[PDB]
Amino acid sequence: IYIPTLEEIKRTLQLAKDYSENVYFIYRIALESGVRLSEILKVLKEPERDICGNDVCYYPLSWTRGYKGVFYVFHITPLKRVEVTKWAIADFERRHKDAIAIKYFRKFVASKMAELSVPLDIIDFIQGRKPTRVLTQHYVSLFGIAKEQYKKYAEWLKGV
């Protein structure tokens, strides 16, 4: 399957930033977090609920598709308020065929976390996906395990 290259990500961030720094910031949080666009737009409408701790930040959210459950938007950069819909994003990509669709930023994040040996069930949780197994491998302490695993992607990302 297609996983974007780091260069393809950089070029997309740059196209965005030159179009709107707000749209850019959305792609940036997409790269930092691995979560899906809808969640990124939720957290940016209420950036105050963000929680920043030392090395990384995390924004507590709750599953809406199906039974509810707590997950976190992990990121490095403190949030700022951005008010857009998915249509702002759609317009931007329609106008830039060589900008990688934001949905593919997930694939890239997932792929990198693999190379850093983040276990797949934790990659799933970091990205705001529901468990694939009823009997999860990490019953305690899920937040801690996720955070320490995420701190490895953060370090990588910080050194580019």
Image (cartoon, grey):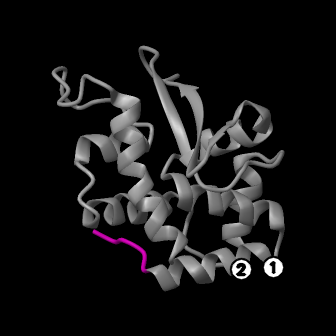
Q: Could you say which disc has been placed on residue 76 in the image?
A: none
Residue 123 percent across, percent down from the top left:
33, 47
Q: Is residue 51 magenta?
A: no
Q: Disc 1 designates what residue?
A: 18
As measured in the structure, the alpha-carbon distance from the residue carrying label 1 to the one carrying label 2 is: 5 Å
Q: How many marks?
A: 2
Label 2 crowd (10 A; few <14 / some 14-19 / many >=20): many
Going 46% across and 65% down the picture, which residue do you hit?
A: 155
In the image, taking residue 70 as reference, residue 58 lies left or right, namely right
Q: Amino acid at mark 2?
A: Leu
Prevailing SS of the magenta stretch:
loop
Residue located at (30% from left, 42% from top): 122
Local secondary structure at mark 2? helix
Element assignment for label 1: loop
Magenta range: 1-5
Q: Is residue 74 left or right of residue 16?
A: left
Which residue sits furthest front? 54
- Quadrant the N terminus occupies: bottom left
Instruction: Check if mark 1's residue and mark 2's residue have beta carbons within 8 Å.
Output: yes
Name the foreground residue: 84 vs 134.
Answer: 134
Q: Residues within 10 Å of mark 1 (few under 14, many from 20)?
A: few
Report which residue position mark 2 lands on.
15
Reply above or below: 16 against 73: below
Q: Amino acid at mark 1?
A: Asp
